[PDB]
Amino acid sequence: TNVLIEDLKWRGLIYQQTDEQGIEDLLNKEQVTLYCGADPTADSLHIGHLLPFLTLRRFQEHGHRPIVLIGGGTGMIGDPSGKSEERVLQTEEQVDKNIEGISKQMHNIFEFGTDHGAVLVNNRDWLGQISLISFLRDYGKHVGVNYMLGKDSIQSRLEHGISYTEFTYTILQAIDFGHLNRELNCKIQVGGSDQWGNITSGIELMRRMYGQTDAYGLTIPLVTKSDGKKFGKSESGAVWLDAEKTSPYEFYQFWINQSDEDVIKFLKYFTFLGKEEIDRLEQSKNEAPHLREAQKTLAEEVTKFIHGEDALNDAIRISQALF
Amino acid sequence: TNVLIEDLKWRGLIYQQTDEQGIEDLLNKEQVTLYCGADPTADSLHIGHLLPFLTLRRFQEHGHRPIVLIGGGTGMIGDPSGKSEERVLQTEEQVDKNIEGISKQMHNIFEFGTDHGAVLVNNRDWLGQISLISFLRDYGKHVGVNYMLGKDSIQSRLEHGISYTEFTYTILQAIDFGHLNRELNCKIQVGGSDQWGNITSGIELMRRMYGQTDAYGLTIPLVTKSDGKKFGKSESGAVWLDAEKTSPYEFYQFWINQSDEDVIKFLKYFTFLGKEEIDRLEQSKNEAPHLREAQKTLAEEVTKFIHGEDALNDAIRISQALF
Ligand SMILES: C[C@H]1O[C@@H]([C@H](NC(=O)[C@@H](N)Cc2ccc(O)cc2)C(=O)O)[C@H](O)[C@@H](O)[C@H]1O
Ligand SMILES: C[C@H]1O[C@@H]([C@H](NC(=O)[C@@H](N)Cc2ccc(O)cc2)C(=O)O)[C@H](O)[C@@H](O)[C@H]1O
C-alpha cells in the first residue's frame, strides 16, 4: 500500500537509508518497531531534537511501534559525532538531573504507559551491567578498528586527538540497537544525519555477532533555513522546549518568523496537517503573503503541541501587543 | 511539465534546496543556466566529485545550460568547508599544474567549445583582477560577520583557530556566483552538501548588493554505502578519474564490488539508464543476485563514460583473469 513511505517522501523526511528497497518492503509487509535516542547533555531538548521524534509519531500513526531511548549510560560518555572538540565528562548527579528533565518532555510527545504502544527506555539499564572484561569478550571481538577508523563521524576529531573513550562511543550505541532488536524486536533506528555512523555500527555489530541481517537505519535531513543560517538558534541561543528556558512566547515567535521560502517545508516537517490543507496554505502564501497564514498556522500547531492551548493563547496575546 | 524534477527526485539526487517551489517554477518556466565548481587541490578529480557534475548533465539533457568552474583563484586559498584543519597554501605553479589536469577531465565529461552549450570558466580570471581596497569597498561592505559566524561550514574550524583567510573563502565563492549571474545569467548553483554555506553566501551577497532575488541553490546528497563506510575510498586511498593514478581495472573493480543494498541507488545516481531498464535490473537483483547483473551494468556504464570503450574491455579481461 506504501501509504506511509509516500507520505514521508512527500514531506521530504527521509535523507539516508541503509537499504531502500528492504525498508520499503519491511514497512509494507509488517508492523515495525523502531527507535530513536537522545543523550541527556542538558536538562531540556531543543527544536533540533524535534524532527526525528515527531517522525516516529508519523510511523506510529500507521501502526508501527516507537521506542524512545534516553542515554543514561551513553550520556556518561558523550557522542563525538560531527563535533570538533572533546566534551568534558558530566557528573552522575547532573546526568540524573538531565534525564529527569528530558524524560518529562518525552511524556508530552508520546503516550507512554500503554500495553503495546510507545516505550521509554534508559540505556544505563543494560550498559551499566556490563563489565570491562565481558564487554571485550562479548562485543569488542566483533568490531574492526579499520571499519571504525574509515568513518565520517570521527575524522573531525581524528585530526585533533580523539580519546579512546570518544572513539568507543559508537560501539555503545551499537550495543543498544542489538539489545532493543533482541528484546523488543526493534528493526529500524532513526536519527539525524550526524548519526549515520553510529546507526550503521549497530547494524554491522548485529551482523557480525549473529549474522542478523533484518535491521535497517534511516536518517532525517538536517533542517536548513533558506538563507543558510543555522536552524534552531534564536536571538540569544538555542530554542528549548522547556518553558522555563524559552518561554511559549519566544517559542511561538520563532515559528511565526520563518521565511516564505521555508514555511511550507516546515509545515510538512513539523505538523500533522494533511496535504490538502498544506497545499491551500501554499496558495495563500503565493497569493496573499502579507497575511502570513502559513506562518501563523505553523506557530499555532507546534506551540500547542509543545506547550498546550493555554500557553499558546497567552503567546498570541503578548505577540499582538508587542507589535 | 516537471519531467526533470520528477526524474531528479526519483533518482534521489536533490538534498537541500533554498526555495523548493521557486526552483520548480523556474525549471518549468524557462531554460536555466547553472553552475558547479571544483578547486584544483590535486591534479585529478575523484569519484566524490562525480555526482554533482553528472547531475549538471541531466539538467543539460532537458535544455538547460551548465557552467563548470575551475577554482584557479579560490584554489590559491583553500575551502575550509567541513574540514577540521587549516590547509597549507599551494604554490602558483602547483595550482597551474592541477588546473591543467582537472581541465582535461572536464573536457571529457562535457562538450565545451559550442556556441551556446556548456561553458568552462576559471575564477582566477575575475578574482585575480580585484584589489584589496576594491574588495572591501565593493563586496565586503555587504557581508555581515554574525551572518558568517552563525554558519555550519566553519564551526568545525572555529573551535580550532580558523585563519582570517579561510574565514573569507566563503565570500570569494559568493563573488563567483554573483559574477556568473550577471555575466551568463546563471541562476542556480549546485554542489555537495558541504557547500551549503558557500552557496547561500552567494545568494545573500547578491541580495544585499543588488536586491537580486532570482537565484537559488541545490545540494546533492552525500553518497553513502549501506555499511556506513566512506564512499569513494578503495583498498589504498581515493578512486581517481585519472587513469595514471587509478587504472581502469581498479576503477571498474570499485563499481563491480558495490553491495546489493546500494547498487540500484548507484545506477540511479551514476548512469543515464532509464527507469524501465533500472527496474528490470532491480528485479534481476532480487531474483538472481548471483548473476550480479546490476553491478556489471553499473561498472560498464561508468567505466566507459570515464575511460572509454577500449579501456573498459581491457578491464573486463584483467577482471576475468584475476578471478
Ligand atoms: C534526536 C536527535 O538527537 C541528537 C543527539 N543524539 C545523540 O547524541 C545520540 N548518539 C543519542 C543516542 C544514544 C544511544 C542510542 O542507542 C541511540 C542514540 C542528542 O542531542 O542526544 C542527534 O545529533 C540528532 O541527529 C537527532 O538524532
Ligand atoms: C564537485 C564537488 O566539489 C567538492 C570541492 N568543492 C569546493 O571546494 C568548492 N568550494 C569549489 C568552488 C569554488 C568556487 C566556486 O565559485 C564554486 C565552487 C572540491 O574538491 O573542489 C565539494 O566538496 C563537493 O561537495 C562537490 O561540490
Image: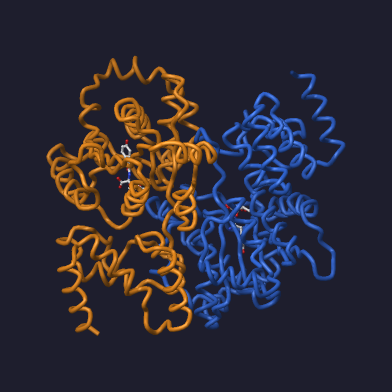
Chain colours: A blue, B orange
- Identify the residue shown where x is 39% and y is 33%: B187
Q: Position of residue B292 (x, y in %)?
A: 37, 79
Residue A120 falls in image quadrant: bottom right
Q: Say above or below: A261 vs A15.
A: above
Image mark count = 0
Instruction: Residue at the far front: name it.
Output: B1
Q: Position of residue B8 (x, y in %)?
A: 45, 52
Can the viewer see residue B164? Answer: no
Could you tell whether A53 is left or right of A305 in the image?
A: left
Residue B73 falls in image quadrant: top left
Q: Position of residue B298 (x, y in %)?
A: 33, 69
- Identify the residue shown where x is 65% and y is 46%: A268
User: Quick one: A6 or B45, which is closer to the camera?
Assistant: A6
Screen quadrant of the N terminus of chain A: bottom right
- Identify the residue shown where x is 35% and y is 61%: B271
Q: Position of residue B199 (x, y in %)?
A: 41, 37
Split into quadrants, the picture shows ligand 1 in the one at bottom right
User: Quick one: A48 or A157, which is closer to the camera?
Assistant: A48
Screen quadrant of the C terminus of chain A: top right
User: Quick one: B252 or A201, which is closer to the camera?
Assistant: B252
Can the viewer see residue A115? Answer: yes
User: Quick one: A15 or B167, which is closer to the camera?
Assistant: A15
- Identify the residue shown where x is 21% and y is 37%: B115
Instruction: Residue at the far right: name it.
Output: A310
Q: Say above or below: A137 vs B217.
A: below
Q: Say above or below: B202 vs A110.
A: above
